[PDB]
Image (tube, rainbow over all chains, first blue to last red; front, top):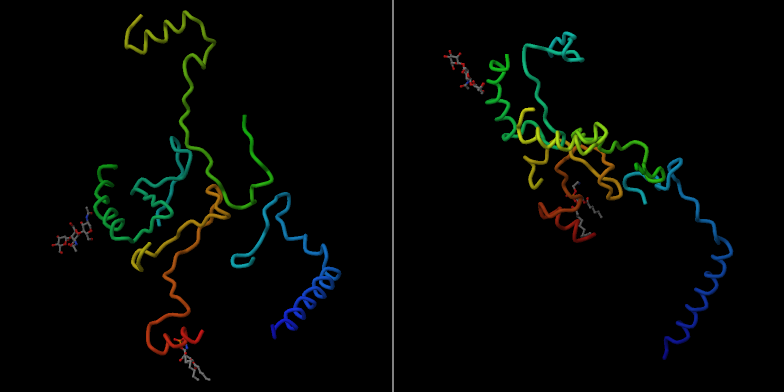
Length: 48
Length: 49
Length: 49
Length: 48
Ligand SMILES: *[C@@H]1O[C@H](CO)[C@@H](O[C@@H]2O[C@H](CO)[C@@H](O[C@@H]3O[C@H](CO)[C@@H](O)[C@H](O)[C@@H]3O)[C@H](O)[C@H]2NC(C)=O)[C@H](O)[C@H]1NC(C)=O
């Protein structure tokens, strides 16, 4: 019960940054490197 | 280092003084198992000739 | 019918080329008859004629 | 190749699990960066 005022504050802090983050970075991360004329993603050896 | 005359009946440069050796790629040469073939198999170059 | 997918060959890896034997048959090197399958069977079992 | 005397030469790596697309890489007897090999070494690992 004492922790309730905290766990209500964590929820209203994820909802701000979920909204803000969404507005700032929505749809941006859909352009990775690709080999020309192919669908193989082109990364280096230990890179994700 | 061999000397490699060019030839007919082979359409490539060749040496008639010894035999070449093909080791496959994922096989290491210098392994005792491989090193010991190149020892005993070396007596074929006289019968080859 | 040869089908290769260009969308999935990364450019510099070198797949295997070929190793198959060139097994053309006598009834496929020439137009087939019934009077040639007689000739062809008759000289698989080592006869003269 | 289970020991150092074997782990010499080249071996083929295969990219994205495709057996038709391979590259040669030299093979070496690597040693882990955090190991238990003297006590000082063991302690660093424990700290991590
Ligand atoms: C496999 O490799 C070994 C090592 O090179 C070869 O053994 C060597 O064979 C030659 C001729 O058979 C030996 O030469 C002889 O040396 C003695 C003195 O040691 C001399 O008295 C002879 O007149 C002759 O010069 C050579 O010494 C020998 N090496 C050893 C360490 O024994 C062997 O011939 C190779 N096998 C094949 C099939 O080629």
